[PDB]
Amino acid sequence: MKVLGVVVEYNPFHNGHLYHLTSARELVKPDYTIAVMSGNFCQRGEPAVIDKFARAEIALRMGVDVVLELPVVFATQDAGGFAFGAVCVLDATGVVTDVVFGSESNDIEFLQRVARILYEQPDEYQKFLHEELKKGYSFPNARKYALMRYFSMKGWNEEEVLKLEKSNDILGVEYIHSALKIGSNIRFHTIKRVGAEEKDTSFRGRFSSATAIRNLMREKRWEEVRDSLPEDSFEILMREINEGRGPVFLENMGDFLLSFFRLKNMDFFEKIHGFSEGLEKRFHVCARQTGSYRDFLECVKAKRFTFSRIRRLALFSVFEVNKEFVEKSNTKGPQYIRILGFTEKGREILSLMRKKAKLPIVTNMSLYRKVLEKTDLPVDKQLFLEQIDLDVKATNFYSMFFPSVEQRCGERDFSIHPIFLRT
Amino acid sequence: MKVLGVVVEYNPFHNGHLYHLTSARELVKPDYTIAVMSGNFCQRGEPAVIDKFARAEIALRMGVDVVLELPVVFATQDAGGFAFGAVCVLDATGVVTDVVFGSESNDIEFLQRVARILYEQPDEYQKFLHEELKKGYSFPNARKYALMRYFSMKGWNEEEVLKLEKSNDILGVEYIHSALKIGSNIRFHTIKRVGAEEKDTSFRGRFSSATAIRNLMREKRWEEVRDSLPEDSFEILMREINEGRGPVFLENMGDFLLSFFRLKNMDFFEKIHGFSEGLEKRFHVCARQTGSYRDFLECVKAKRFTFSRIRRLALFSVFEVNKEFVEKSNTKGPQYIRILGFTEKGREILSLMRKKAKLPIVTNMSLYRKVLEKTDLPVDKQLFLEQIDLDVKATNFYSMFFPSVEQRCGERDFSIHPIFLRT
């Protein structure tokens, strides 16, 4: 049979995402569609505009059969751990055959060559990369340059590597690389991304970028927002807004983040994952000097530091995510498959997953301890506990920023139940 | 000569405080007046309405010659450590002879008897207290009851002990007890407190309680506030408000405190000072269940838990103040005398203090390391560093809640300089 896996965020779900899903499904023509989705926190280092349950419901109503949660530790990282975690989950399902993503290049063979190079790690490219790293650049630039040197050395075209400056292509290459790391049989497909780039903050019609739409939400223009969204997506959006669970933006968390950083000392950041190049110093100082989170991001950021990375380090710092645990997670991968939602068609493939899963499947949250105790699968139990605790902590922290105080009460992992769509 | 020490908070400074200072100075007729004052955080577990520098300036302009800061670790505790720290500082000055405080009982001999009992710790009273503690009460009630039993056993009147249910009397008894603990020669005096009780939240004329005046500030009634304050005090108040450094209330910190508590686990609170009777549990749960800080305080509080104690534990939890460090501080006492301010008359007695001080004196904050290194006095250096770091951290955290973002920038311990009043 054919089961189409997809790696998604949907912050929010717009017409471009619908077009993507449609074209992908029509390309594969699968018997099922499984979607691994980010939680209440995305990759950019920004919180989701609405929580994961509403977005999972939207995903289900847009033609996704089953919605799985990507663990927060793999969600808030850069392309490497993100792709690692995602591919690991989709492979851990056991039923996933095909996986389709968006791309600017629309060249799969090229991305596969690049991923092959980054996987096999030839001694040549390692010498080059060693040199460029010693030259004082950052990792993305050093890897780009070294790959260009390898491509010129092998007689190929090094101007092709420019294609890899696009976000989706990086994500794809890292996907393939991860699959080659854990040895997944999953077939990967690319479809040309049509719309505004993810780094484009300006609104033009549809399909506007997620950032542009979020900005439109900030300005309280709901007509352009409604024009940029499908009917059901906009409906669920306004539903979550009117009940006081949204919208949620980073600047709301900003004061908390800064005040929390002012409390911590130099060592704390040296413990937290992703801290190097004296970023512990810069964090410690800028936290005390700046009066707001925007100014903080401006201060910490230099020519060599992107907004995304710094935001990621902020989220890693606020949850006390430490290098050791992150290393274990980046080695063994996720210890579980969390089920966010399913349709009536979803119960089928999910039931097959109950058999073919390489990882413990979690539906009822209150029972997850029982699941970890009664599972025949040989998983690290401590890593399991720490990961799921990080997920619950992330959701619980996300809940506080609900506009309505009444909605802030209780733990929404245990209280809320997996979204079930009747047909 | 005669130097009058006083233990104060001034949140804010009102007509009652002026009356107190006047009557005290007229009682002692000293040659100098030294005031040990709480920092940006008071005993009740609430932040000061305005920062410590403005309040120190007010204190200086109201006839206090020198203003010293009580270390945050002794400021945010209950009566025992508060009195301990205060008495320790005033004694550490070396120049302090007399100390006057307010009282409902206006009986010094009685408080001295009580303090004598609590100091010498007779075996009898210890058996009684052991029994009442085993009976399942809390410490204040058990001590009150045991003291009543001792007073009845010794033939004295046990209905006198009722006097000790008043806040000021508790503070006084603990003062005397502390002085008897570290062997201070300081003479203690009591003057009848005239005005509303500190636990009275309703506004009547003058002298209204500090809480009543703060509540009047919350309601934006500035005429009643102006009527409840001296000219200079009100002037400095409005000065700090208009420049956007005030007012500061606990509910503003509430969201931060709750969200910060949701991040921490069971063990964290077991590390933090003042946690027992399963308060770690209650904290861990109520933090996740409640949506606001008021509801949190309501939840954690039971028949046996006062608002003050819980607020104190909140402040202790947010600064990561741990039992060990607090024990060391409650043993050796403060390691330094921080100078908040002085007048031209203050330089004299301060210069004498440069000689007779039993503890290192700190004026310039940027130089405090140099001071700790070049001091001939035999003080614990690590305890010194940890304490002063806790002070700076407290101020830095307090700065974030300034209404004006522009005022949130920088560390105000190092940037701001000791208030100097020219005559």
Image (spheres, coloured by chain):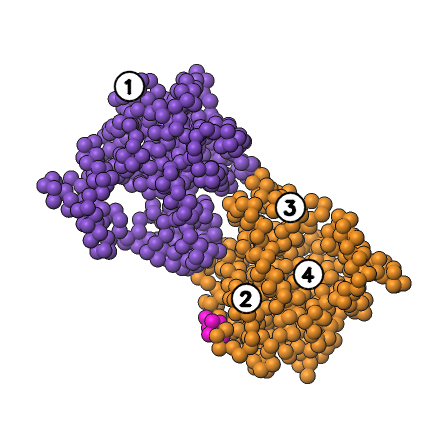
Chain colours: A purple, B orange
- Amino acid type of disc 3? Gly
- Give the structural element (helix, strand or loop) at label 3: loop
Whether residue B78 appears in this view of the structure is yes
Task: Kindly report the distance in space between the C-alpha atoms of the residues bearing marks 4 and 2.
Answer: 21 Å
Q: Which segment did they paint magenta?
A: B366-371
Q: Position of residue A366 (x, y in %)?
A: 54, 31
Q: Residue at x 52, y 77 (%)?
A: B375
- Amino acid type of disc 2? Leu
Given this view, does label 1 or label 3 mark the residue nearer the observer? Answer: 3
Q: Are marks 2 and 3 in contact (CB under 8 Å)?
A: no
Q: Image quarter for residue A248?
A: top left
Do marks 1 and 3 share a subunit?
no
What subunit carries mark 3? B
Task: Kindly report the distance in space between the C-alpha atoms of the residues bearing marks 4 and 1.
Answer: 74 Å
**Numbered mark located on residue B69 in the image:** none
- Amino acid type of disc 4? Ala
A298 above or below A164? below
**For mark 1, what is the residue?**
A29
Residue B244 located left or right of residue A82: right
- Amino acid type of disc 1? Lys
